[PDB]
Amino acid sequence: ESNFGVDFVIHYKVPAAERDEAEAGFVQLIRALTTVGLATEVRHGENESLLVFVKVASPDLFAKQVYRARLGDWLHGVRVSAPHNDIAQALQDEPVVEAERLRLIYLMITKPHNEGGAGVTPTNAKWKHVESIFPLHSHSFNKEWIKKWSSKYTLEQTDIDNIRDKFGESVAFYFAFLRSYFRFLVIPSAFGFGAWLLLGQFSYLYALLCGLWSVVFFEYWKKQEVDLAVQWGVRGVSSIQQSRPEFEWEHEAEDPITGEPVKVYPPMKRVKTQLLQIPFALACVVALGALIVTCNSLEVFINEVYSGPGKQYLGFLPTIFLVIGTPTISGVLMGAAEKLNAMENYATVDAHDAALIQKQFVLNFMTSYMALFFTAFVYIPFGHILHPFLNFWRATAQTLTKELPTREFQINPARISNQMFYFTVTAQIVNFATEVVVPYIKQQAFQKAKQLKSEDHEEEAEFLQRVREECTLEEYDVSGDYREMVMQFGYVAMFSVAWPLAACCFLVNNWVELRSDALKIAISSRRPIPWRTDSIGPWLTALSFLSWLGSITSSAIVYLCSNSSPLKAWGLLLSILFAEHFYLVVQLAVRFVLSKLDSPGLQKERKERFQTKKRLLQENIEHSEKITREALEEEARQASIGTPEEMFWQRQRGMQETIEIGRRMIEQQLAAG
Amino acid sequence: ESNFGVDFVIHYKVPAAERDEAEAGFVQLIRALTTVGLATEVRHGENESLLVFVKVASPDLFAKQVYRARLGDWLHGVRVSAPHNDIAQALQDEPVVEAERLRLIYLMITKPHNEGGAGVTPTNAKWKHVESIFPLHSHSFNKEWIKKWSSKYTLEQTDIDNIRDKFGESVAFYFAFLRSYFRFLVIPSAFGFGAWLLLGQFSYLYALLCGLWSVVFFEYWKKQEVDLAVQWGVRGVSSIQQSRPEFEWEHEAEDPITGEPVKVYPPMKRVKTQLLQIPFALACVVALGALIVTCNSLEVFINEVYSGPGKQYLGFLPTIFLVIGTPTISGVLMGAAEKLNAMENYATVDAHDAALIQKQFVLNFMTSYMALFFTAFVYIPFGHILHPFLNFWRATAQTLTKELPTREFQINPARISNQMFYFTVTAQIVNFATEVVVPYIKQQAFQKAKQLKSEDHEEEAEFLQRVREECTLEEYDVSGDYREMVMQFGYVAMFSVAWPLAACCFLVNNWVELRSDALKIAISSRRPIPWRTDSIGPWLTALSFLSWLGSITSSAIVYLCSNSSPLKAWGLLLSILFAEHFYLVVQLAVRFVLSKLDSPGLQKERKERFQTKKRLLQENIEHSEKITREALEEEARQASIGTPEEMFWQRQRGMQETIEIGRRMIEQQLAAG
Ligand SMILES: [Ca+2]
Ligand SMILES: [Ca+2]
Ligand SMILES: [Ca+2]
Ligand SMILES: [Ca+2]
């Protein structure tokens, strides 16, 4: 029903080996926790673990730290205004939300000891026994949240603000991105269904209208991202995160803006190491891309040119050979990339996580579209370059057992429609299996293992059984649901011209996905620690790269596929050159139009930043004789001791003397004529 | 030698007609001027004019307005910090420069009467008799300035800061731009001379290295523009200018940021009118471009295919027919553009002047490069499409007087070298004539007209003769010297691949031009009113358009000209597509590298904006029992009246009780195994 007012849960695995040192660390832990100012409780959890429940003891002592955290946000420019001069008045204007409370408790348990409470981050390895620090769910809210989101057709802005109030900003930006992406998916589903009825397959008019859509959505999200940023009070929070515990710093120096001592690193030594990302990425497209092509070279031999026995039995040979390789070789390439960003020496935890994405994006670019790059550019337009690869597999299949029967090779034009039919409606359903219900069935099977093996009080018995169940769940990553939506945006921007019902079917997926990822937070993951992010992250560069490449590839397809005369190469370069420059001129139009549209987000900051300069300010016929007072003064001060320029101003004094002298010169100039 | 401490000079033409109303306006003028707080002097000037000399009377009264102007800059976010709390201390930290003094005196004489001093702007037409308000030169400074700049090889940063201190920012940004452009012109003069010796004419390697230069200069200037902005204290001064006196405003409403009543206009009504700039510009390239081509169609008939008498006599027929048309038809197109921006309803004077440039740039794009667009793309690669135009002029010359002798048409490959030889070394010298010495000779001839026609005091006689001479000089426009330097940047970015000694010869021009435009302020123009600009203006979009088009056209030339096999069109599109994307990937590299380089300009603002929040802030084993104090308190407050979750926290209190209970559960879990 409800938690026992508990803020956080520390798992603290205690193994058989190093048992006395874990107990000595257990005394060292809870004596460190009680000095921060939070009440502790230890309970019987798993077979070798001790659930350490913590809440903050004094709310008045806690209200001081909230006031110091809100002041620290405004001191660095994050908050739009200063807090109130009276304590507990700014807490009464806006209260502490459940997300901001769990963030400051987590920063009490995870910060260096000199500047903060206790260093219970497990990455320090002074204690390797702390398994995880995680907050608890409240199942009264999750039953209300899934019921409310499934009942409504759309989501109001106040519904996503409930996610910001309880699950932090970094979770709430995903649902804010997914809602704005689902509503902007209505537009290319409209003429995407229209280009399926009026126009033919591979319409050139659709490829220009889709390239218009991919930049009017992406630029509008950049306007709505900074609008949601200052609305939630989270703006410019790139620099405000604690540094990583693993960080090599050349010399500690003075901070330029902050004026405190901070560990600084020369960025040109990092740009020297950041230059190595290009020899890493070019090894990625060869290690993965030659693997995708070769298993695509297999299927074009088994399916089309083959008339032997067990044709469907050998039809699963390319697929089951592909799903073995791609998690294994990308697992290797994720290993070297993890040693690359560790070598890159990222200070804050956000920049370390974001550049891990840019290495994780290149692999997931190659597991996604390399099956469609080979079909759209090598199989369909000129499959006769594939004939020596068909001459290879014809030689090796003769060595199996007489000659095996082959048909003459014919380019099947329905391949890219059938390949897109996998990625649009078939891959989405099996992903809907793997995202929610296959974890939910696996939670049932792990529950029955507890019943196979088959001390608490009257009210703690169901609660402690819930926390032990909640603890084995993995931490939710908001990166994992960004990868699914950006790769889905890749199919619309690059490859929806080959199958214009893609945006119509991706639309009905994201209505489910907006309520299925909400269900994934509820029952299939423990609550993540509420982090603050000013932006969506590094995905803006990922969305802009697919949008720019979507202009090239969707227009290179529609020249190479619509003829299915024989592919003059000047037409291919011209079909790119007009459409790639059509993307740039429209991007210059949409960026200019939204620049002229008013931003209500930035104005509410600029209104208060002006007005806070005003409140610092507000706390801190008779004028002709004053000129004659000065004219006597500039005489009497300089006549005591130059004198040519002094006498020039004193020929005429006051006003009415200078008028009547000027009146004579109008007479004197007119009298000569 | 020196001025008589005079701040400004009002000319106030008084004609024969409307003479009594001009005298009544003269009383109305100088009675309005004396209420602002400035001493006035009227003197005998030109035959129908009255030189009204003004200075501010009381420096203590003037110091109040400087303090109100410096506070108004900080209140809008322009100034990096607030002024001092003590009056005349912030004037003692930084003094009033001669540029800031003449700006505030000019805003006293040019502002509406309710919010300011007097509306003596002549555009109001309540008085049409005020000819000009202009400050005076100081010839002691100008003799020192021209001598110092001609003596040194380069210019230090402190030399340009002397121009900011006396001629305002908007003049000083041109010399700061020209110095940074002259020093960055060393780079393409280096390999531009190298591509003239090692490589041949039309080198492809030069066209990539020049496109690298045009973006590493332009992005570095955008870094140096915001660096010079906050250094001079002029930053974000786009919104701070007074509105134009001619401005239609739909309804006066509340200002969002400023919170004062201001006249607002809906910007989407302007974007509706801003959409008309494209049907205006496409009429510009046809009215001018068909004029440039037709007079180029004449010269290709007279010079090459003709053997009649008076060949050099008819050789000046295309040139003298061209210099008649282009000032006249662009004078028409400047008239409609002046009615276009007037229809566009620009509020501030900077945005009205900047969008006049973007219409004035399109014409000066077409007077400059249309002679080179026809040569590089129509004459050299396929001159056989020009043969029907040669068939036209062959028909009309037979009707003059027997058949006139024609040679067979041969494409001269030395045309674009001879055409660039005009624009690089020949057009620069005649422009050096027309810029400084032809105005200087014309000032001598206008001086001798005064001696042909052939009342003052002992010291005013040479000074009043100087002011009457200074008044007839035109106001200096900083736009006129930006047009020469941006068009010079067009020849380097677009057309220097055809003649690689262009950047070598443009380098030796800008050493002269940096000291010739400095001489143009001194003797050939009255001092402009010192205006403040945060940016160089709209020329950043002009420099970026030539840099992007410089990637296309210099690479389309080197395919179409190097063959001078027969011009396969797939090579032309590929030579663009690689080099135009080479421009984009290098632009993404240079923008990222300068983003990682530290900006010392923005940090000095962010250091003080943090510290001014700190000064608002600064003016306004024993902790375990406090948890047990709260644990008794949360008991005794809730035991007076829920109770399950209350009793959960009170099973264990303090620290040492919770330790020893946790010590048993390590025993109890290990005892079962
Ligand atoms: Ca899914
Ligand atoms: Ca997801
Ligand atoms: Ca010149
Ligand atoms: Ca100039």
Image: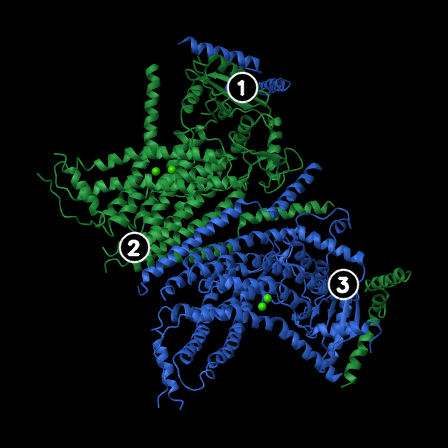
Chain colours: A blue, B green
Q: Quadrant of residue A31?
A: bottom right
Is B37 situated above or below A27?
above
Mark 2 and mark 3 residues within 8 Å of each other at the beta carbon: no
Lower sequence index among marks 1 and 2: 1
Name the mark on residue B558. 2
Above or below for B346 versus A590: above
Give how far apart the Cα atoms at labels 2 and 3 are: 71 Å
* Count of number-bearing discs: 3
Residue on which the image places disc 3 = A36
Chain hosting mark 1: B
Q: Circle 1 sits on which residue?
A: B29
Residue depicted at 34% across the width and 78% down the height? A408
Question: Chain under label 2?
Answer: B
Identity of the residue drawn at 36% across and 55% down? B209
Ligand 4: image quarter: top left
Question: Is residue B382 visible in this depiction of the protein?
Answer: yes
Residue type (three-letter) at the residue carrying disc 1: Leu
Between the C-alphas of marks 1 and 3, the distance is: 74 Å
Q: Secondary structure at mark 2?
A: helix
Query: Marks 1 and 2: CB-CB under 8 Å?
Result: no
- Mark 1 and mark 3 in contact? Answer it, CB < 8 Å: no
Residue A617: give x, y in percent of width and height.
68, 38
Q: Dot 2, how many residues are within 10 Å of its Cα: few (below 14), some (14-19), or many (20+)?
A: many
